[PDB]
Image 1 (spheres, rainbow over the protein chains, first blue to last red):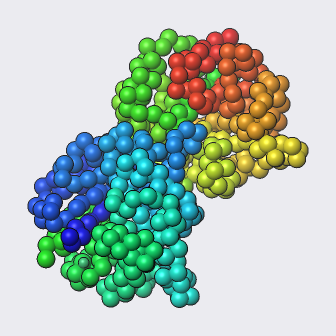
Image 2 (spheres, rainbow over the protein chains, first blue to last red; image 1 turned 60 degrees about the vertical axis):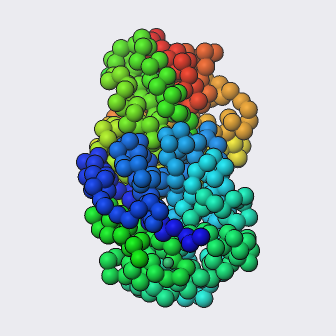
Image 3 (cartoon, rainbow over the protein chains, first blue to last red; image 1 turned 180 degrees about the vertical axis):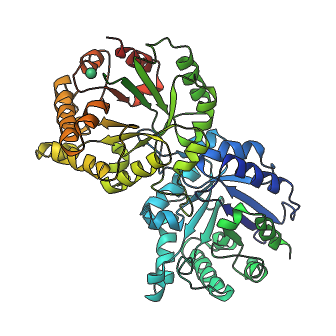
Length: 250
Length: 250
Ligand code: NA
Ligand code: NA
């Protein structure tokens, strides 16, 4: 069965109570393709997770932007996966490029987070991606395979995993990734999954594009053979997020 | 005037909606010394900050357990100081030993957080403390002074700062640090403020003890000349937190 298009919206470290109410209302009024056609996840900061879950339309789902690597306890400042389950938050973003780079989350740390989140019943958007230095060194697939392998070695089930490829080398560097460049990485990543995990896992796992997506490139990006949707950054705070969801209609 | 006793309760990475309701109800029914005698702050995980703020007695105050180093934006998983202000959360804990050690927060990173939080109008519990290895090397005051200096170099107004000394070394040594051991560090820390900031800042800044506090030592610790209260860990989840608040009555 074909992979269901997936659109996640990462709000990052943004939001006020008034802004969140506006974003949620605009999402609630949106008219988008059916749940059979597209799966929509929105990810507010921790402090807004109960508010968004309590007010968002029930056919869009809520994600935390991170969670802790293991059971709760003496980890001041962290939020455990079981906390998210207690609050009926079904999804979590793990390994986002900003946490790998600015907060120095290693691939093994991320992989341990994915496994623990899955073991608590969460669904995971697992992020991978190479930097500009890594791409110019010709290490793109070496880096992305190593990041993916660290996850693969630690999980027991891929059913509730979505992989997000982030072309970090293009974000904020001035460079711009083409739909062909994105398809190139996605194809190779899915090929890695078929070889190293299983053909079934490669065929069924959504691999979403985490680079710059707008009205101009959304159709061409979403139509790529191995691109199954988007992990949206800043546009997820804006009405145009709805336009990006509408790319699922083909 | 004498420094007002200060009792902070750090819930760390603990709590369910059900357990939070029980904790808050027990706090709300507590009968403790007057607000002139003791200042009480409780610190839930991010996802419970709105819930606790909306239900807790107005004479106890709410703290976040961490916040981001600067303005919000592209920092997936982080919570900015201006978010805390937007949610009417007045306090934040910064530099907790678990974040310095496990999450590798540097003294300069902590210092920049303290300054940014103060600039946004938050009050700050700034945490310092040496490891077992550092204490056994003879570097207790070298370490505590260096951590404090990184904050002092970035802070111009200390009015809304409380310093918490955490004897991190006492977890490894399995030792109940004696009241004399707390007093000697607190005294040297206050003397450091007098010489490196000002006599007035030394005289007015609360320095609270972040080691293990129980019925056998709460009076003895609180009665020390340079100990102005407690930063409680796991006991803050339990009714015994109220007995620690009651140590302010002398
Ligand atoms: Na596609
Ligand atoms: Na005292």
